Image: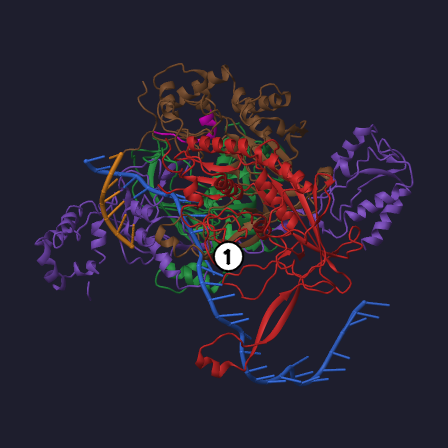
Chain colours: A purple, B brown, C green, D red, E orange, F blue
DNA sequence: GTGCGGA
DNA sequence: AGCGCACCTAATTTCCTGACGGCAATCCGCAC
């Protein structure tokens, strides 16, 4: 009906001012599947010369009200609604309230419940609160972490009018925020937080991604006739070697901090594949693609050339690669 | 002597997969040559073609619908796609990170050791190497492919290659020599005889010249810009680790009613697959009931149920008693 | 020997946590020292006696999971939720909580003191760094594990140090105003988490991870920090983090 | 008994089309010679000639109007345009990305099998190859052409060429041998007798020397400047994949009021043509009402209506019900 | 299996 | 080797488009 609905509201408000507690730290803000009402209310002092920020060295102005279920949430709506907050009225009654209060319920004495509300207390732990070990003096202590709601509200308001880096997290829904049971999370469900990243020249891109990869030639030395065991006998195949190196190495110049080192295990491996235990006379190992124009240190980028043939390649490139 | 599951029990993963990166190559020069693949932006003009109530349909049937998107395609000179990822295999009895009660630790260690005695993790490992050989980690990239080859490297030994189009995606093979040789090493790592194994997988998919590649799509919530956002790993396209792992755990063929639906499903607690919207293992053959019949009321279960329970322990998760206040 | 220094060079971590209730970015320092203490505990069960009493954190590259908008801001991403234990567990769609993830390349400097500090110790560390994680993230590859002697073998990068003087000495009524003003004056500083404070008293509750130890409910504490290159660093002791425990306070400090 | 469509239903595309790249050639030497075509930047001074309120017109009628634009033109030595693109064809029964009820999947598979039994996807495929032969994928580039030639290549066989200025755009031919031999292979790929088919298409358009070429234009969403921006594919001019594919789905001649307007329309859910400003399938012959009259309440529909439903399942889309 | 309660 | 200038300055005006539209689905624990 109408003028008959107001009965249900003030019926429900007085039936649920016993399940609404006072808190600064709530447990369901980490995971909303944690059973019960676990949390803490920190009412201690401020040092202000200590080197660290906590919930007791910042100026937080509004406490928080917490319930277990979204059903028992009408006191939080009640304390937040006048013509000229309801909280400030019930601290110092101005009748402005008392006049309007007593003419619909005849029970404002009971409701004025919202004043000496009990504090939230930590009594147990579950699998949904983060528990870690910390070394204390030869043994360990088990620590269960409860996040701060009052500090999250305070940071998000003070970052809204500032120009330091910030990130907005958009991950909670309306129905998920209600299930937490806290007033300050149902109003701020998408908070603003600090951005704490390393300097901006140390971020990954594709230029840093391709400077850690190395090129290989496209010629199996074991199928190009003119090469025996691993050494070039012909003299005509030389132009093909000089060209391959040029093609694959044209502009990929690299500085020293970016070139694969010349290991000793690799020049041994090559030796084995074809027999020799030591490098035969007049022959010198050579990379088909140079190791300063970007190349690999592998068995698939190595050829043994005669001592004069190595002199031709080591200078013809030098002109083309300046 | 044991009345319930402990108050904090947690298992970690034993098959840890890293992210994947895409490259473009050519098939006749695929052992020597690779180029980067990049994600481009694309905007479209569309029509309003979704189901609407009859009042709105008479007012918005012929309105324009601009939207934002992103895409990835191969070049006009390359015809293949190269994907590289890696797996790390760790033992099962050392993947328990928390257990409040000591007697439950003793009982579960005994049960894993009896499962090492009979079928020492060899069936499941063969199924995992089958899902590496079938190339099921190519979700929409396996459709329309001329040649698919997969190469598996363990340590410094490169094994002979696979022809992934010669395998069916519903039947598990137990006769290939290469699959058995890899599966023995993965089984011995699972059993505790070895302490770690590192696997490196390379796949080559021949699609066509300028055809479309399908990367992994991100979950981002921004109110201003709603569009398709694709995964960039170090500037290049790739796939998430979760998709590759979900491809690898599709080994379950022991659910209650398999003779009608004859396909393998992923290994979950209540048999929940994101394709069919009815759970396949709803009550009697769930994980919790079988694990509270294997440890708490000592019983010998059939070997298929033991296979399912050990598969859940290789997948990992938070497995504890219902939480009271 | 007895004292010594070991370098873990160029470690790649994928999917580490990057959320500490007011900060999205670099993980908290307690995880980076937790990696070292876990390495000590696994090395002391293989009967290689060693004790790590200091960690240095050098940063070479980073990437945050998400994208950057046109206006220059960061939007983060999350994986699709699966099945979470609780009441609504047999449902097909689960709920989305608050999370953030980062990728890092880093190098660690460890101060070890034991009965013998040789290259066999480095091999023992190499056979143990393939089972651990760093900050909830997997390790993909590393370059080398080696012993250093001086400040000329350390590779090029940027270390993270504590700057608490630039916070305690700024203008404001409360500490959060001090942090905001100190970040507006110097634009090379970052906010970091440095440990925990106490909200209760030590005792035994019901529902613990290990039911035979001592418990205390805690809250995280935050501070300031900044970056300094390797070649401009004075000593090898002005970049080493350590554990310190007062009564009610669990901290990590460079001092 | 099946009441309602499933909560998650989505079909994937069975006719994928790549992007297009533009080249410039000469007609007599066209099998041996090709050069790139690039987009230039052109800025213009104009006059204020838009319609204005009477007060503003007395203050802004004789003011300059600088604007930015872009343009593409051929060279002074070339006379022909070459466009290259490719098509991949995939089977219809293996193109359902999501379906959350196993009975609805069985029903869809049975109806597609009956359709394969009656007509093996041959009429629709003949229409798709006629749009390749008509050169309808050259929107403003077909006006003012001397010779248009289109070549189709499957695997390593080049089929005999097409004269695209001899095909009417309102009439579908069914007696050409080349169209039939390509259409049989597309039909066999659509039925399931072959797993994939890749088709590559090259077209030559003679338009003259130094004349204008019209590429595709990019969409701008406010937060960006409102100047004209044209599509660059690998540094050269090109067309979008979505624009080519619309020209190939203009095969619908089965709408309710066709006997008055006798032109083919593109295939859409509510039959919305943008050229003529009328929706042609708003109620009883839409996709949503026809798919709920074939599967949920078994009822044999005319063969014209089936042709439309199977054409929607080659395009794709999200067809999901809420409850 | 139901409806609830708020931003 | 060992160097690689001193002085001054970089114009003014009139403007910078009109239209339409920017998806459907899903992400809630808990008393009773």
Pick whichever, B241 or C132, lies toward us: B241
Pick whichever, B69 or A307, lies toward us: B69
The residue under the point 50% across, 18% down is B116
- Which residue lies most toward the front here? D259
Q: Where is residue C232 in the image (x, y as percent from the top left)?
A: 60, 56
Q: Where is residue A83 in the image (x, y as percent from the top left)?
A: 19, 65
Q: Give the range drawn in magenta.
A: B311-320
Q: In which quarter of the image is residue A228?
A: top right
* Apparent side of residue D22 relative to residue B292 in the rendered image (left or right): right
| Magenta-colored stretch includes residue A240 | no
SS at mark 1? loop
Eyeballing the image, is B117 above or below B150? above
Q: Where is residue C133 in the image (x, y as percent from the top left)?
A: 51, 37
Pick whichever, A76 or B58, lies toward us: B58
* Apparent side of residue C192 relative to residue C233 in the rendered image (left or right): left
Number of numbered tags placed on the structure image: 1
| Magenta-colored stretch includes residue B319 | yes
Is residue D21 something one can see in this rendering?
Answer: yes
The subunit letter for the residue under badge 1 reads D
Eyeballing the image, is D121 above or below C219? above
Q: Dividing the image into 4 quarters, which one contains the C terminus of chain B?
A: top left
Q: Where is residue C211 in the image (x, y as percent from the top left)?
A: 34, 30
* Apparent side of residue A280 relative to residue A3 in the rendered image (left or right): right
Eyeballing the image, is B9 above or below C226? above
Is residue C155 something one can see in this rendering?
Answer: no
The residue under the point 28% across, 33% down is B324
Q: Dividing the image into 4 quarters, which one contains the N terminus of chain B?
A: top left
- Name the residue carrying label 1: D274
């Amino acid at each position: 009906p109408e003028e008959q609905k107001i009965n249900k509201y003030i019926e429900g408000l007085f039936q649920s001012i016993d399940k609404n507690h006072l808190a600064t730290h709530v447990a369901k803000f980490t995971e909303t599947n944690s059973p019960g009402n676990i949390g803490a209310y920190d009412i201690l002092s401020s040092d202000m010369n200590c080197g660290y920020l906590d919930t007791a060295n910042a100026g937080w102005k509004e406490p928080d009200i917490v319930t277990n279920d979204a059903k028992y949430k009408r006191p939080q709506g009640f304390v937040a609604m006048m013509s000229d907050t309801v909280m400030e009225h019930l601290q110092e009654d101005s009748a402005e309230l008392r006049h309007e209060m007593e003419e619909l319920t005849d029970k404002y004495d009971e409701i004025r419940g919202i004043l000496n509300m009990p504090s939230m207390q930590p009594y147990r732990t579950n699998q949904f609160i983060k528990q870690v070990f910390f070394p204390v003096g030869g043994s360990y202590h088990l620590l269960s972490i409860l996040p701060s709601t009052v500090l999250n509200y305070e940071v998000s308001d003070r970052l809204y009018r500032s120009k330091i880096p910030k990130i907005r997290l958009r991950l909670l829904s309306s129905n998920a925020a209600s299930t937490t049971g806290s007033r300050l999370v149902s109003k701020n469900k998408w908070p603003l937080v600090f951005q704490a990243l390393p300097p901006k020249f140390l971020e990954k891109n594709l230029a840093k991604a391709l400077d850690k990869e190395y090129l290989l030639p496209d010629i199996n030395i074991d199928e190009l006739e003119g090469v025996d065991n691993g050494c070039l006998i012909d003299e005509a195949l030389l132009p093909l070697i000089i060209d391959e190196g040029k093609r694959k190495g044209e502009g990929n110049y690299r500085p020293r901090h970016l070139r694969d080192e010349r290991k000793e295990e690799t020049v041994q491996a090559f030796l084995d594949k074809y027999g020799y235990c030591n490098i035969p006379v007049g022959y010198e190992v050579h990379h088909i693609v140079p190791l300063s124009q970007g190349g690999a240190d592998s068995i698939k980028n190595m050829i043994m050339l005669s001592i004069e043939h190595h002199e031709r390649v080591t200078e013809a490139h030098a002109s083309y690669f300046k | 002597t044991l009345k319930s599951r402990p108050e904090n029990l947690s298992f970690a993963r034993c098959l840890n997969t890293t992210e994947a990166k895409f490259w473009q190559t050519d098939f006749l020069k695929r052992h020597t040559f690779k180029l980067p693949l990049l994600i481009t932006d694309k905007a479209v003009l569309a029509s309003k073609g979704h189901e609407m109530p009859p009042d709105k349909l008479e007012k918005e049937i012929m309105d324009p619908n601009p939207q934002k998107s992103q895409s990835c395609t191969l070049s006009t000179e390359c015809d293949t796609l190269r994907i590289d990822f890696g797996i790390k295999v760790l033992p099962v009895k050392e993947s328990m990170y928390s257990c409040s009660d000591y007697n439950y630790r003793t009982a579960i260690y005994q049960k894993i050791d009896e499962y090492i005695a009979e079928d020492g993790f060899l069936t499941l490992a063969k199924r995992y190497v089958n899902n590496i050989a079938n190339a099921r980690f190519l979700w929409r990239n396996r459709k329309g492919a001329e040649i698919i080859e997969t190469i598996v490297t363990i340590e410094d030994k490169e094994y002979p290659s696979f022809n992934s189009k010669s395998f069916n995606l519903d039947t598990f093979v137990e006769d290939n020599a290469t699959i058995n040789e890899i599966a023995q090493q993965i089984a011995d790592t699972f059993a505790g005889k070895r302490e770690y194994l590192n696997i490196y997988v390379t796949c080559f998919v021949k699609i066509g010249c300028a055809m479309e590649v399908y990367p992994s799509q991100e979950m981002t919530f921004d109110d201003d810009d709603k569009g398709k956002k694709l995964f960039k790993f170090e500037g290049s396209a790739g796939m998430h680790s979760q998709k590759i792992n979900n491809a690898l755990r599709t080994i379950d063929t022991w659910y209650p009613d398999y003779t009608t639906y004859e396909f393998p499903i992923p290994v979950e607690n209540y048999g929940a697959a994101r394709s069919i919207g009815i759970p396949f293992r709803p009550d009697t053959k769930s994980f919790y009931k079988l694990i509270d019949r294997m440890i708490l009321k000592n019983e010998d279960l059939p070997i298929e149920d033991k296979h399912y329970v050990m598969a859940i322990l290789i997948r990992g998760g938070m497995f504890s008693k219902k939480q009271e206040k | 020997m007895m004292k010594g220094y070991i370098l873990l060079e160029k470690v790649n971590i994928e999917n580490a946590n990057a959320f500490n209730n007011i900060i999205v970015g670099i993980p908290a320092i307690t995880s980076f020292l937790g990696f070292a203490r876990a390495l000590e505990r696994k090395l002391n069960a293989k009967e290689i006696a060693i004790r790590i009493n200091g960690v240095g954190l050098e940063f070479h590259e980073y990437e945050l999971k998400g994208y950057k908008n046109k206006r220059g801001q960061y939007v983060t991403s999350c994986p699709l939720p699966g099945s979470i234990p609780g009441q609504n567990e047999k449902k097909l769609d689960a709920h989305i909580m608050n999370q953030a993830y980062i990728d890092l390349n880093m190098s660690f400097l460890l101060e070890v003191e034991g009965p013998h500090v040789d290259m066999s110790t480095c091999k023992s560390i190499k056979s143990t760094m393939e089972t651990l994680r760093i900050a909830g993230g997997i390790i993909r590859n590393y370059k080398k594990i080696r012993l250093i002697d001086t400040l000329a073998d350390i590779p090029y990068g940027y270390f993270l140090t504590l700057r608490q003087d630039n916070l305690n000495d700024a203008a404001g009524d409360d500490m959060l105003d001090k942090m905001i003003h100190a970040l507006q004056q110097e634009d090379t500083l970052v906010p970091i988490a440095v440990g925990f404070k106490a909200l209760s008293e030590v005792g035994h509750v019901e529902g613990q991870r290990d039911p035979e130890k001592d418990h205390c409910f805690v809250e995280s504490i935050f501070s300031l920090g900044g970056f300094e290159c390797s070649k401009i660093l004075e000593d090898i002791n002005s970049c080493l983090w350590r554990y310190k425990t007062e009564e009610g306070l669990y901290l990590c400090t460079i001092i």
